[PDB]
Amino acid sequence: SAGLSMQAELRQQQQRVELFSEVTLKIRQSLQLKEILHTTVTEVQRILQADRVLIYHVLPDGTGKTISESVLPDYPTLMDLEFPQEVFPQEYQQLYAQGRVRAIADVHDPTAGLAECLVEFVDQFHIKAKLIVPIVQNQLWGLLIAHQCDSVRQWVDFELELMQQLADQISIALSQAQL
Ligand SMILES: *[C@H](C)[C@H]1/C(=C/c2[nH]c(/C=C3N=C(/C=C4\NC(=O)C(CC)=C4C)C(C)=C\3CCC(=O)O)c(CCC(=O)O)c2C)NC(=O)[C@@H]1C
């Protein structure tokens, strides 16, 4: 007789082929999502003519890392850098989860009210001006951030509004698609 391979090793291999098809699609989806986020920060940097645009991801214990960045070559890269909770306190992570935004024309202007240690931190990256909008899943997932490094910058309301609208679509992706 015969047919022993059909319901043994050939059907085993067939399940493995179907799972391989599915795992390669899932990895391509991870690549495509990171490409869309990368294209978004690079295009926002070009369109704003900002010196840096990045996506900062916070973990539940409030530590963080830059997951996407576009930076002009005259200024430091935040891509590889991990930071503790103290650079962005959990009390403020909660205010961002509840929709806090900031548009700071001049981080060195005392009336902007920034912690001395925070002014020192943003100085590490040659930051003069910063625009900050949250990405949520509400729990904070991260920040979409624009920096000016060459000069102080009076941010315009539409820049803040449309940065928020981009971050809100990142929030939907990270939530409704469960991506
Ligand atoms: C003190 C030793 C440390 C510290 C304290 C601190 N930070 C904030 C608030 C913020 N910190 C950040 C962090 C960033 N901004 C960026 O552009 C980047 C990427 C380069 C990061 C990581 C942000 C966005 C905020 C929120 C600012 C806001 O007012 O909404 C506070 C609270 C606010 C205040 O100014 O008192 C505090 C106390 N931050 C440091 O970096 C020090 C090491």
Image (spheres, helix red, strand yellow):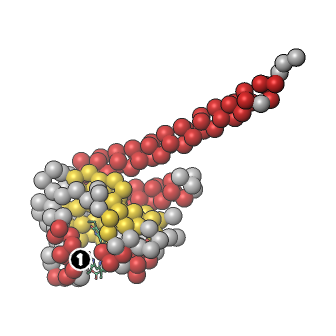
Q: Amino acid at mark 1?
A: Leu
Please give the residue where the numbered disc 1 appears in the rendered image. Answer: 118
Residue at the farthest top position:
1
Q: Left or right: where does residue 94 sit relative to residue 13? A: left
Q: Left or right: where does residue 154 sit relative to residue 99? A: left
Dividing the picture into quarters, in which one does residue 119 lie?
bottom left
Rendered view: 8 above or below 149: above
Residue 160 visible within the image: no
Rendering coords of residue 68 (x, y %): 34, 53
Task: For ligand 1, tell me if the residue under mark 1 lies within 8 Å.
Answer: yes
Q: Left or right: where does residue 115 sit relative to residue 39? A: left
Rendering coords of residue 13 (x, y %): 68, 31
**Ligand 1 quadrant?**
bottom left
SS at mark 1 in the image:
helix
Rendering coords of residue 37 (x, y %): 39, 49
Dividing the picture into quarters, in which one does residue 77 lie?
bottom left
Residue 108 visible within the image: yes
